[PDB]
Image (spheres, coloured by chain):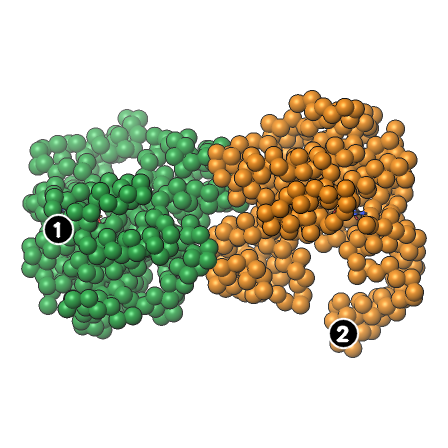
Chain colours: A orange, B green
Amino acid sequence: MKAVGLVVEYNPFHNGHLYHAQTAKLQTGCDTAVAVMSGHFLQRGEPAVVSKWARTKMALQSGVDLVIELPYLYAVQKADIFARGSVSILNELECEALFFGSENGDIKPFLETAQLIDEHKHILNDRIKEELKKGASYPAAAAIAFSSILHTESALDLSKPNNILGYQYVTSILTGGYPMKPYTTARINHIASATSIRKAMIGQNLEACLRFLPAASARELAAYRKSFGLWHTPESYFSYLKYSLSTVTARELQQVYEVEEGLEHRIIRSIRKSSSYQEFMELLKTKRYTWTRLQRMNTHILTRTKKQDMQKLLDNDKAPYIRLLGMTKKGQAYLSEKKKALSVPLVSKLSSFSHPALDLDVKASRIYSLPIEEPLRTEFDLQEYGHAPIRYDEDEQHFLN
Amino acid sequence: MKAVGLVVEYNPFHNGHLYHAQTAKLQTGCDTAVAVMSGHFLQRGEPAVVSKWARTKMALQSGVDLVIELPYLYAVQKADIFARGSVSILNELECEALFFGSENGDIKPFLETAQLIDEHKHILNDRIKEELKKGASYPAAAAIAFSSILHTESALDLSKPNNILGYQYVTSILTGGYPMKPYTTARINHIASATSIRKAMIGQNLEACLRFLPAASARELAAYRKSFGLWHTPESYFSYLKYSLSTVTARELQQVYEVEEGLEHRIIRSIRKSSSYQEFMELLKTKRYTWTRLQRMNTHILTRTKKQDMQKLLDNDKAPYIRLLGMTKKGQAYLSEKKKALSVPLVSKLSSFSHPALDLDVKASRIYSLPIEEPLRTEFDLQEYGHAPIRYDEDEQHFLN
Ligand SMILES: Nc1ncnc2c1ncn2[C@@H]1O[C@H](CO[P@@](=O)(S)OP(=O)(O)OP(=O)(O)O)[C@@H](O)[C@H]1O
Ligand SMILES: Nc1ncnc2c1ncn2[C@@H]1O[C@H](CO[P@@](=O)(S)OP(=O)(O)OP(=O)(O)O)[C@@H](O)[C@H]1O
């Protein structure tokens, strides 16, 4: 029994993710598609459009045989970390293959690059420090030390996000020596981006996207906004940002993960004067901050994730548990074959196991429902517990729950 | 030139608060009424229905010359600390008198009882000893001891609220040593209660309660609706309380003012399944905790105010500052006269002092404003720092700002 690992956030799951889930089992020759998926808040930092449950349902119907949560711990993080944790989990489940889309359909410049870099790493740090002492900044001196190599005609721009994430998966693998072989391909009824789609739904358009989405995906989104009366946007949580920053002191906000020393003053000062999440952001920007890092920071503020929480939990080199979000027939059989093999707990009912990282995913799960109006919100908050793990019948369409 | 102090929440100012003020000036023989007022969160633990700037504007034209904010420090407390703080504020302001309403026009029985409990305090306490030793609860013992000296029919009714408030005022003037003379009248355009007028407005219908409202009150009220788009209810804040108990740890929740040892768990159990502040209060209520005390707790859980900060600030024997909301030309005169004599700062613009208790005040407002739909919330927020004292001219209608 063979599975291919898929590092994903389906937000929503679109034609590109569909083609990638069919080609996964095609090109990696594994009978099973196992995805680790960001739960509620994601790597880009934003809230998911729809809960991890219903996105699970867009996935199980599009050819993903198994779906596990990527803990907030790994999910909302710099890609170097995000990659590590995700691949880590795909290896605990013993996925022999890994498969990603990318701006370079060629795996060879990925492998070549990483191998090349570790081949020279000493050179890299000598030239980095040789620029640094000359007064160069961190990313500059790194950009220079790195462009001292790799800059040949190869391209594979690692200025491109998928090349980044993919290089980082591959790096996590090699570094870890995982017996999981990586694969990649380029990205192109039709296909537009998850984000173009998203902003198109923000623009009061859903079926406009239907060419860009499979059936299950749209069918799912519709029932979500139907039930809870919203698509979740970063802006939707602005009040709770305001509120949350309203009660905190400087020293306490200093301790939140991804808040650099001294910036707490700027944050606290700016949130007052910002009638918009956008204004808030522009008031916050420093060149030591990407925009995604600012979003991530804002999430950590929202969920009150502390430097010591995150750093005492990031230390470990294995994954704390496996959260099972959903499974197919194939998925079920795979999880059954390898069940006893897991070196870490398999969490189905939350009741079974309690963990600080788990406590953190639940935390995010409660923060997620806040823009939901009640009674709907109180009922939403049930799903993290008394939700029996989703199951779906691959052959002719059945959910057994 | 002699001042009569009033202890008031004005929620909102109605024709009866008008009775209070004008009867005050007339009965005490003072030409100046100074009111110390709970601003955005009141004695029983709930929010004001309209901003303290507005209600200041109301009273200023209804015959109050000075409006001083009762710090949150003393405002959300049971009657004795509430009265301790407000009476310290009035004593700082050199009021010859303190005029409080009850169902009694007679100032005497408050005096008689006051001295009675004041002198028997030894006897009373010693009598609580024996009763706790027999196995009674403390309140039981308390009722038993009070009953021995008190049950003579004086008859001071400690049931009717404003009577209790009266008694504690008398008590504070007594142990404080203030040169203050308590006065009083029976409470009774026949006036209607503040609350039923609230329910009126809440029901969106402000038209039933008019004849009971001074005109300016009606104006500034509807002006607050039209300006900021709501009347404030406790339920407005439920979602935010729901955020607060999400982002707190039970150890952290134990340090919240009025969360007594061990209750934080009942709290957390109750919040996740409660769709309303009502239901929440319902599951929460205990014998150890009355409705209003729980509203106080829930409020402190909103402001996330810690116990040690609180104790620190309650330790101060006089009010940390005198906070100026508004003044007439008379109030301005009286102020300029007694200002030299104030022993703690007079605050007009917020930049004029820094104290932990004022931080508390400003944060209380920052929480208060949240229900306002953004950007209007931000505009409102600009006031606490923005608004300098509201100045009315009794020679009719000149506001100078
Ligand atoms: N059209 C496409 N072609 C090829 N690969 C694709 C793809 N769309 C996604 N993938 C790959 O499918 C995997 C899942 O992508 P996530 O679920 S992490 O979302 P995302 O891809 O960043 O969003 P998007 O860019 O708006 O589509 C990734 O490795 C992708 O490279
Ligand atoms: N109609 C009236 N007659 C006499 N005194 C009155 C009065 N209305 C108010 N006062 C006095 O005015 C002062 C301020 O009362 P707060 O502003 S604290 O509200 P509250 O009166 O408790 O509200 P309620 O009980 O729901 O009606 C008190 O000394 C009152 O005795």
Query: Which SS class for mark 2?
Result: loop
Which of discs 1 and 2 lies nearer the camera? The answer is 1
| Mark 1 and mark 2: Cα distance apart in space | 74 Å
Sort mark 1 into few (<14), some (14-19) or many (20+) by Cα contacts within 10 Å.
some
Residue position for label 2: A136
Name the spot of residue A357 as percent of width and height, x first. Answer: 66, 41
Which of B120/A319 is in front? A319
Asked which quadrant contains residue B290, the reply is top left
Q: In which quarter of the image is residue A142?
A: bottom right
- Residue A224 as seen in the image, left or right of residue A326: left
Task: Find residue A118 and report its horizontal and vertical position in percent.
Answer: 89, 58
Q: Residue at x 63, y 67 (%)?
A: A286
Residue nearest the viewer, comparing B137 with B248? B248
Position of A219 compared to A263: left or right?
right
Crowd around label 2: few <14 · some 14–19 · many ≥20 (10 Å): some
Residue B317's mark? none
Q: Is mark 1 within 8 Å of ligand 2?
A: yes
Does the rendering let one see residue A164? yes
**In the rendered structure, the residue with mark 2 lies on which chain?**
A
